[PDB]
Image (tube, rainbow over all chains, first blue to last red; front, side):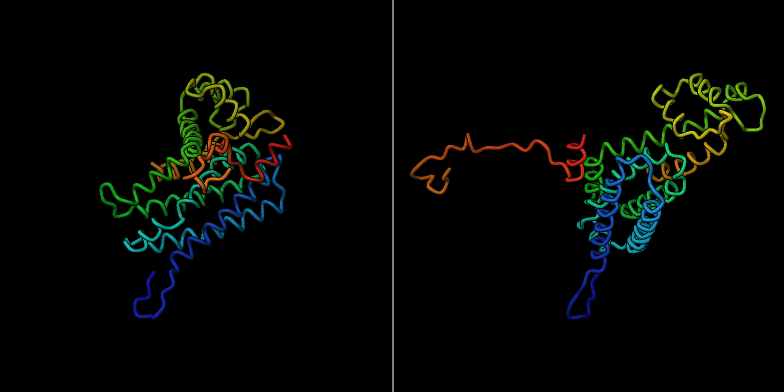
Length: 241
Length: 35
C-alpha cells in the first residue's frame, strides 16, 4: 500500500482494483454481445473461461491483501472503485445465472461463473472482517447493495427456488410418485411433483422444467439435477446470508 | 439564451431547462433500436 522509506510511493492495492474494474467492464461488454444470441459458441465459451479465471485470480489477490485484517488496505478498497466493479459483476451474475441454466451445453461455464461469485462474496466478507458498528465500509456496502437491489433480488430468488428443490426431492410425495429408489423420474411425474409440492408457483415450475434436461425417454436424473443446482446454491447462499 | 448578462437582462430558463429520462448503454440502445 505505502512504501514508507521510499521517496515515491505507488499504490499497488489501488492499481489492482483498477485492473479489476477494467476486466469487469470487458466481461460485461462480452456478455452484452451474447445476451441476444440463443447459444454461446465454443470460442465464446473459451473466452469467458479465460476472463473468469483472470477475474478469479484478481479477486483472490484482493482478498489476500485484506485478510488478516489490514485496516489501511480495507480503507483503501472502501474509498476505491471496487464498488463499481462489484455492481457490474452482480448484474452479470444475475442475468447469466438465469441464461446459462436453461441451456444444457453450458454446465462448465455455469460452474466457473458460480465460483467467481463465491470468490467475490468471500472478498466482500473479508472487507467487513473486523468491522465496527456504523462503519464507513458497512455504509458503502449497504449503498452498493441498494444500487444493485434488483440483481440481488434475482440472485436470491434463483438460490431460493433451488434450495427448496432438495426438500421437494426428499419429500415422501416424491417417493410415492417414484416408488423405485433408482433415482430416475419422468418429466410428467416431476411436473406433478412440483404441482403437489405447492411451494413452487407456475413460473418457478416452468423454469425448473426448462432448466431440466431430459432424454428422448421423457425422463431425467433428478439426483444429478439437484446436485448441480443445489451445492453451488448451498454454499454461495450461505456466504451471502 | 444569454445568462452572462443576468444583471441587465433576465434569462428565460423556462425554455432552457431539460430533463434526463433514460441513460442506456450503446449496446442496449442498438439492441432496442433493432427490436
